[PDB]
Image (cartoon, chains in turn red, blue, green, purple):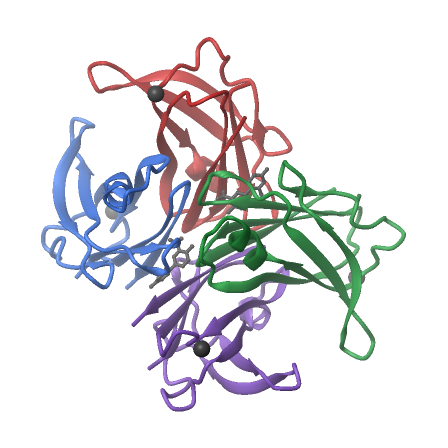
Length: 115
Length: 115
Length: 115
Length: 115
Ligand SMILES: O=C(O)c1cc(-c2ccc(F)cc2F)ccc1O
Ligand SMILES: O=C(O)c1cc(-c2ccc(F)cc2F)ccc1O
Ligand SMILES: [Ca+2]
Ligand SMILES: [Ca+2]
Ligand SMILES: [Ca+2]
Ligand SMILES: [Ca+2]
């Protein structure tokens, strides 16, 4: 699968499980159309978001519902969500992993692009 | 100064200078109203975005134009921008520092909220 | 395997491959004795460092040779290495993943502890 | 002030106050000589560690006592400390800011080097 998401919890030192993730693609009219979504597994990973045929070049937005994650744990969060926006460009075979590390008042995200 | 933004460059180990920052506020009709904008200084800091009177309760979006930053350095970056979304002043006025650390394929953001 | 290391490159958006990793355990005389070592694979992962029988409770040090990594890429690094020091404590079945995200002037590390 | 340290708490979104910081310098006999130490202030900043005259070229180690910080907050953290090791002033005197962002199972560190 060409697009995978991984979410970690920096407070409990664990995968962030059951985190809702929504993927949008930028449309011609510059609005965000829903493209794919899911929830992270017990490993904190979300697989099977899309397929190679559907994942074309374009501008994508990945919204991670961090606020619901923290509220389910009884921990007070700062952000409404974590939003990752990027251009996917074919430059040879590419697989994208979007990884996020979450704290109540901070998040880090990084992209791992492999052949 | 109720809202301040600080941006660092993890590649060169320096302040990220002249980074454009745009602040939006969610309006009654659920759209993003432009609220304030500016550029980081030579210290990587952006002061004077707003005032105590203007910075009311609401949902705010801080969009840091990381892509233009890297491209001005001749680097093709992964993200379009770094976007921080949060509810402000829900329990009275606070002072918010939004700090961002930038790499071409990664960023971290953190919030410092003081009374 | 009870202890795994994963290293990512925030500049190129990729696994950090062929990164030397050394594990030390704190000895009775408070000196660091060599315990295990290896190099990250093409996925940026180092498996097979130790076994369940050998990985007892104690204070461990994980040294990641970030400086050699950056020098092999022709990129100017700040740190001599990335060093992660922690106490491993049996509290039920535990597997430890030490993950590191590298930039020339910054690194992040996090621990993922799972059952 | 050639060497400054700043520490933030990613859980509470605040400066990490009263964090002990110890600086060592690698000696001729390849041991770590104690060089300077202090505690972060109410702003999370530690100033006045050393002087321009005392901060000569060398390999330095900044050990941030994160464990005592979390334990004073009643939290059992993963790391013993956060340790930053770097060669300083190799091409003349520089000003170094060592910034650290803390979570119970994670930390990030970054260096800001200015002339
Ligand atoms: O920016 C982040 O979200 C991040 C992600 C990782 C990470 C990435 C991929 C993976 F398979 C495991 C990880 F811990 C490791 C460190 C890190 O800061
Ligand atoms: O998440 C981030 O954006 C981040 C921020 C800092 C940091 C905090 C305070 C400061 F004055 C400068 C900084 F880089 C240090 C590390 C880091 O990952
Ligand atoms: Ca193209
Ligand atoms: Ca209110
Ligand atoms: Ca025990
Ligand atoms: Ca010299």
